[PDB]
Image (cartoon, rainbow over all chains, first blue to last red; front, top):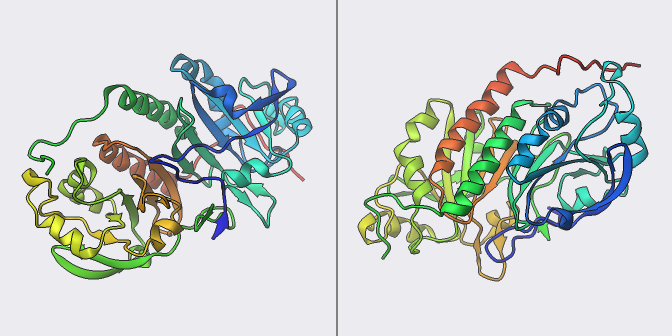
Length: 182
Length: 183
């Protein structure tokens, strides 16, 4: 076992509160989970900036961010790097391993509290897993996907699944024919 | 709180579990390692004999050959005893039962499995409704938490396992405009 902030309560799993400094539009801004209340939030942890592994998901979320906003959804990516490294990464061209200009916030988890709360921190290596969390408009966790490679299709799947959760939120559910409660 | 979901290396191994299941109406011992080499869809649901239809389990059972064809198995688990699971299977669907079913029902009577999986609710004494997809190497790939029975979660699960498997086989390529730095 280890400790984490992912505690089942009631009949749901509330997303743990977080706050920290993010880079938005090239500037530092304090961000918190509660800033996204009333919207779905895709919260994407990735190991580190400036590695030799392409940031496929962040680039694709950035490219498609207007599609998510169109369905009441925001996207925030997070790693244990400082906000100064996030800014430098954005300010480095993609042809040189950088992220380049990006339209989603990069949140800093420098003191590791957020990733420990989300249960994705690796104690030995000092960074997180690659993990995509979908949080609904009530702040409840709906899905976590863990990939060890950068997977571009996970952006498509995220758009599809958010829309599916929202459809379910609104329409409820129907039982199979032939089953009746006792 | 405490759970078994511990990141290790560069991923999240699915916590070991073992317990007694009902399989084709018989009690059998089952454990996570029995599924090595196969994807495992491990579905927790709160309780047998409730007034909430068991839509997922019914659909997984009807479609189980589609999962088996892609080297995937499905196990459902609640905190109920194996005796309760067998009685539930033996109760007709039109009376709130599960009826005959082609997927194992795992008992987590002492709550060890659901605590290890981080889905146990201490106050009520049962689990959340949650679907875990575990790959052929025993690594956790996805967790989905639905409070309502969602039938399409079966179709989605099939599609996601297929996608995870496609990635396993083919790997991924970088966006065209991106190149790494180097030492």
